[PDB]
Image (cartoon, coloured by chain):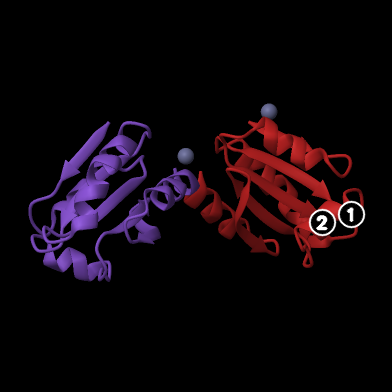
Chain colours: A purple, B red
């Protein structure tokens, strides 16, 4: 499994260049968000089930990245394939997140 | 490296059940169709470049399948991922077919 928690704007772009052959799935979350805390260990369980790169982004730490992907509602999950955003799930729905991964992996 | 040409209605459904964990890309074509003949060898080239299941369906041999996928323009290419239709390309555009394959493979 690979599960990477980012620190500052620019970190996702580096990650994407360094993981070119693989689907990247990003959980945009906030420290004030309860459903984000509930879904966190389940997103970690998915990272152990699928051969993709799982990434966590705190929207208060990566504010320009949150803007780049038009992120509003917490959590939002996006799938990034060959460097482009291809799908999203808005809200804490682990079934939806898994369905999105199956569609793009 | 699988390129499979079907024979009768029901064949696509058995194919999908037997190839459940790979992208399937179906070329719905007709014998009367000029663009279909132009793109055929280029579809075969893609089949030799990508690890997916490539399928050819003559709409006059698999009439109820063509209906079931609402095929109108010839050719039409359909991407199927975990058994659900996830994308299509209407018309003989080999660049857009390859883009579809990359997004879902
Ligand atoms: Zn096979
Ligand atoms: Zn894949």
Disc 1, SS: helix
To which quarter of the image does residue B68 belong? bottom right
User: Do the CB atoms of the residues marked 2 and 1 lie less than 8 Å apart?
Assistant: yes
Q: Residues within 10 Å of mark 1 (few under 14, many from 20)?
A: some
Identify the residue shown where x is 43% and y is 52%: A96
In front: B35, or A76?
A76
Name the spot of residue B64 as percent of width and height, x first.
Answer: 87, 54
Pinpoint the chain carrying mark 2: B
Write the residue at 17% across / 60% down: A33
| Residue A17 appears in the rendering | no
| Subunit bearing disc 1 | B
Residue at 72% from the left image edge and 53% from the top image edge: B39
Q: Quadrant of residue A64?
A: bottom left
Location of mark 2 (residue): B66
Out of B34 and B64, give the one closest to the viewer. B64
Q: Name the mark on residue B63.
A: 1
């Amino acid at each position: 499994s690979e599960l990477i928690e980012l620190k500052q704007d620019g970190d996702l772009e580096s990650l994407l260049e360094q993981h070119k052959n693989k689907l990247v799935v990003v959980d945009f979350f906030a420290t004030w968000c309860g459903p984000c805390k509930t879904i966190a260990p389940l997103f970690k369980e998915l990272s152990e089930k699928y051969d993709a790169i799982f990434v966590k982004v705190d929207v208060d730490k990566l504010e320009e990245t949150a803007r780049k992907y038009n992120i509003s509602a917490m959590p939002t999950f996006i799938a990034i394939k060959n460097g482009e955003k291809v799908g999203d799930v808005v809200g804490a729905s682990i079934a939806k997140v898994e369905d999105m991964i199956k569609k793009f992996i």
